[PDB]
Image (spheres, rainbow, N blue to C red):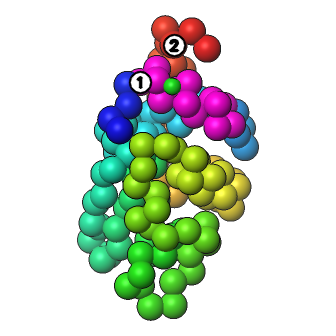
Amino acid sequence: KVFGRCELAAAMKRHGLDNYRGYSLGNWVCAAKFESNFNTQATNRNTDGSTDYGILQINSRWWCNDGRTPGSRNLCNIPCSALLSSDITASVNCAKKIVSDGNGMNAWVAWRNRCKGTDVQAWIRGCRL
Ligand SMILES: [Cl-]
């Protein structure tokens, strides 16, 4: 799925991300916008040889097992390709683990560089939550 902005905000809220570990919903919507352009199927290779998967661009180096990575840490205990569905449950569940481990959202590079410190509430304006 390519989500609309408020559509994704509502889905993320149903999946418990509103204020999860202290991060308001706008943070999560901004992250998805700049990580994946609201796209559940997006994947992106990185310069370190890893790949980011799905709506929240979960990275294969630490978080999911891509089936190649020798000695994969797989901290979310999930195949990376299993993050590529229109249903956001698995990506949300892994995001919850990431933000808990990091005491923050800094692992999301796009969030850290394009969302952090901005008026993230603008991302949920008009969504009637
Ligand atoms: Cl929705």
Most common SS among magenta residues: helix
State the image coordinates of residue 92 (x, y, percent, origin top left): 58, 48
Instruction: Tell me: residue 115, above or below residue 65.
Output: above
Relative placement, left or right, of 39 versus 127 is: left
Tell me which residue sits at (40%, 55%) in the image: 84
Secondary structure beneath label 1: helix
Q: Are marks 2 and 1 in contact (CB under 8 Å)?
A: yes
The N terminus lies in quadrant:
top left
Q: Residues within 10 Å of mark 2 (few under 14, many from 20)?
A: few
User: Magenta region: which residues?
Assistant: 5-18
Q: Which residue is mark 1?
A: 5
Name which quarter of the figure residue 15 lies in: top right
Name which quarter of the figure residue 31 lies in: top left
Q: Label 1 amino acid?
A: Arg
Q: Mark number for residue 127?
A: 2
Tell me which residue sits at (37%, 61%) in the image: 52
